[PDB]
Image (tube, helix red, strand yellow):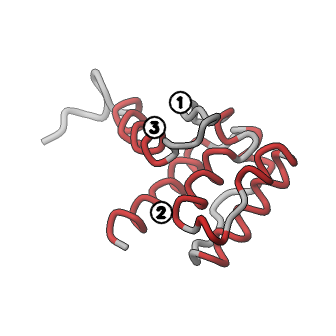
Amino acid sequence: MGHHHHHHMGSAGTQEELLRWCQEQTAGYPGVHVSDLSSSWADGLALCALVYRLQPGLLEPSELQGLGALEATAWALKVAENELGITPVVSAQAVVAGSDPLGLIAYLSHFHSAFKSM
């Protein structure tokens, strides 16, 4: 199958399933909105929310939630890898700046595949 590449849906078609799964996993925190593939990860809320869900006894989202964006990403990314074992795919600066859509989505896939199977 396949016509050429794109015709109606393709890029957004994947983001929809990714954003939907992300919001569901980040659902529970009385003060966290997950509906953006950039700003949502600014303060590292989306990433922290996921990590905390996997290791609630080895995470501190609320701590890095306001302490800082760069610190939240670097801290969550470092601990996430230490607690889960997932090696970072993109730099904190890029994540906080949202200048890496391909990298942000790829990372989410790693976390999803880890929980999808476990």
Q: Amino acid at mark 3?
A: Leu
At 61% from the left and 45% from the top, the residue drawn is 46
Residue underneath mark 2: 110
Question: Residue 118, image x and y in percent?
Answer: 37, 73
Q: Amino acid at mark 2?
A: His
Q: Is residue 82 above or below residue 47?
A: below
Question: Residue 83, image x and y in percent?
Answer: 62, 76
Going from the N terminus, do you reach mark 1 or mark 3 first?
A: 3
Determine the CA span between mark 1 and mark 3. 6 Å
Going from the N terminus, do you reach mark 1 or mark 2 first?
A: 1
Q: Is residue 114 left or right of residue 98?
A: left
State yes or no: discs 2 and 3 in contact (Cβ < 8 Å): no
Q: What's the mark number on residue 87?
A: none
Question: Residue 47, image x and y in percent?
Answer: 62, 52
Question: Residue 4, image x and y in percent?
Answer: 26, 34
* Label 1: how many Cα within 10 Å (few below 14, some 14–19, many 20+): some
Q: Is residue 48 above or below residue 17?
A: below
At 55% from the left and 35% from the top, the residue drawn is 34
Residue underneath mark 3: 19
Work out which residue is located at the far top of the displayed protein and give it: 8
Q: Is residue 91 left or right of residue 87?
A: right
Q: What's the mark number on residue 35?
A: 1
Foreground pick, 27 / 40: 27
Q: Is residue 14 left or right of residue 76?
A: left
At 79% from the left and 53% from the top, the residue drawn is 63
Going from the N terminus, do you reach mark 2 or mark 3 first?
A: 3
State yes or no: discs 1 and 3 in contact (Cβ < 8 Å): yes
Q: Is residue 35 above or below residue 96?
A: above
